[PDB]
Image (cartoon, rainbow over all chains, first blue to last red; front, top):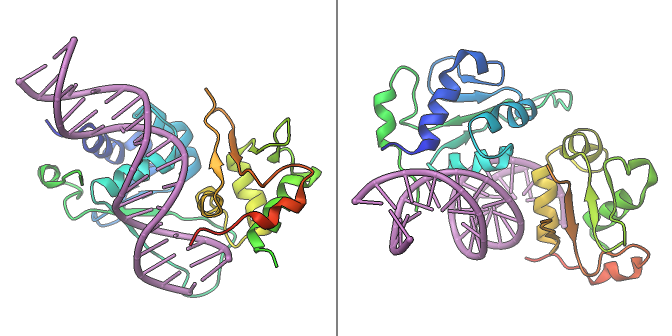
Length: 106
Length: 97
DNA sequence: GTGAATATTCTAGAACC
DNA sequence: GGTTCTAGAATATTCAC
């Protein structure tokens, strides 16, 4: 009864064997994608019918996830990418009961 | 006077040293991006202030380029006025807004 | 099976730089 | 003008009945 995207996202983020690529941020308030490229080509196709980060991000925004922006505020590197962080008020570590409040947009 | 992006794109596709990643398609009517991930990581920042395929693709669409469908099958984009050996045609390409 | 909801893809709007 | 994040639009595909 819960959309497949949301149940798969929870599993993804929660599952320890994926934590190198996708995991909870340090205070359970958001999830991280640590290695976008290996995530997209190895992890995504095991759960979805694609290997495109763009199509994963589309879904995130569709369910109202928002990217957490980190900027540089200082020195620029240029020698390291990302990582990528997304947040939703009802996608929270050790509160899976909140997931039912997440709603697709249109 | 020509937009940075168009003259940079033209350089990228045309330059033999980059053809492992980005090159004219076989009949000069479109270009191909053969290895999206290395293209983006290693080539894009040599010419632009980023390394995101997505930001490159936003610019392509902004200038009216369109992805060619193909019935990961490499990536192909087309613009009627972006044609191999017809660099004169580039001045006809216009940013959209 | 059929009509809707959802998924995936491609392109564009908007804010910011 | 360029880069980023989010959403519109156009198909595919899946789901609930």
